[PDB]
Image 1 (cartoon, one colour):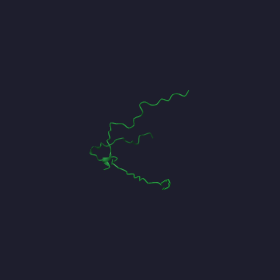
Image 2 (tube, each protein chain N blue to C red):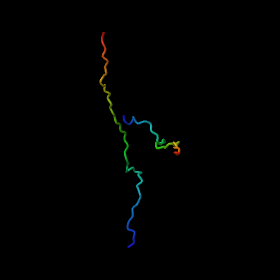
Image 3 (cartoon, rainbow over the protein chains, first blue to last red):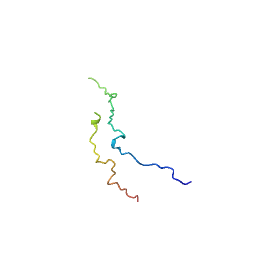
Image 4 (cartoon, helix red, strand yellow):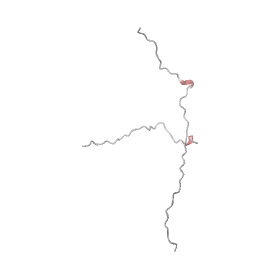
Amino acid sequence: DLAVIGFELDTRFTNTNRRQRGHLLQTRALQFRHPIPMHAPVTLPMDTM
Amino acid sequence: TADEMITKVSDTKDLNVSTKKPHQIADVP
């Protein structure tokens, strides 16, 4: 029982009617916010006289 | 707008270029 039973093709459409569209592009943007704190002081005691 | 933030692009330029003058490591004596 030797026979060819089936096949698959590698054909494709010519997308001249633009039926199919691929991956879409759009612009995005992110914002990052970094506020600056103050930190504990160091002091220098001196006399007022 | 976010789209205007996009800087000049140019397909002519390639960004996968390897080093043209690689560093040649001398054999260890």
